[PDB]
Image (cartoon, rainbow, N blue to C red; front, side, top):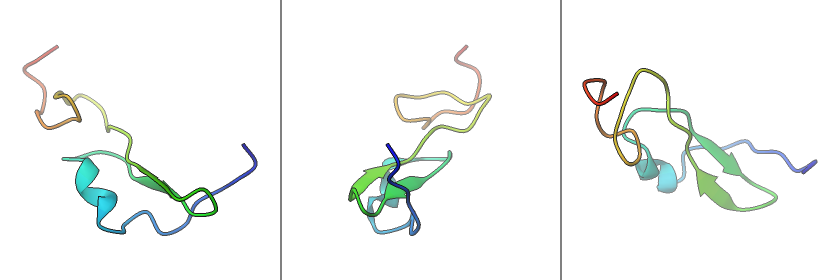
Length: 50
């Protein structure tokens, strides 16, 4: 909490196929959120998998 982020891309950005990206600087923690209307374990697929 409180903590924030800035540089989303940092190599770890590869942890998302097509979704939101967010890297907690102060809390070095690479984590990219999905997007929407997509699919896949990490949002690799795009729809067709409701």
